[PDB]
Length: 196
Image (tube, rainbow, N blue to C red; front, side):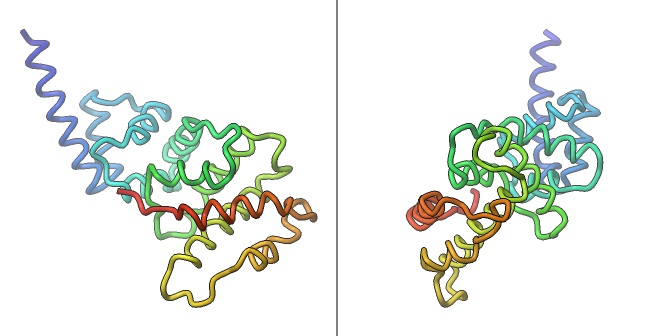
């Protein structure tokens, strides 16, 4: 009756909500929330982003990286959706970066990678003694990926160099070379793939 008719309109409005989001994230979410298609909670918005169905990955990245209190709360709920226990850093990063595309702005990326590092360290408490180590190492992996796989960059970091640039970041000590090698191999053999 009404329910069937209601479900139809809801589904189409949902689709519209998705198109609106892809144009302007905050507007999409507001349309969805106001039409009771989505609860306006950090957890439920994050789940929506995590599922990602019909969502432009650049848009998701844009939303998650905003300064606003809710966007920050969504970002933390979003990374909390990820279970990184016993994944190595590259595997964890790979999964995290599949669900969005990084925003251009430095401040936005910062908040996103900081949320990632906190979650990874929480999921793997023995591994790092600080989120700083995780953060910096995550960007070393991202740079190595880019360094390796961008034509413009003309001398590839070899394993020896990679190990070298990361000295001292493990609370004044180094990372186990074996860890650095695993990361290096992981990235060389399966490079990060831009999200589709």
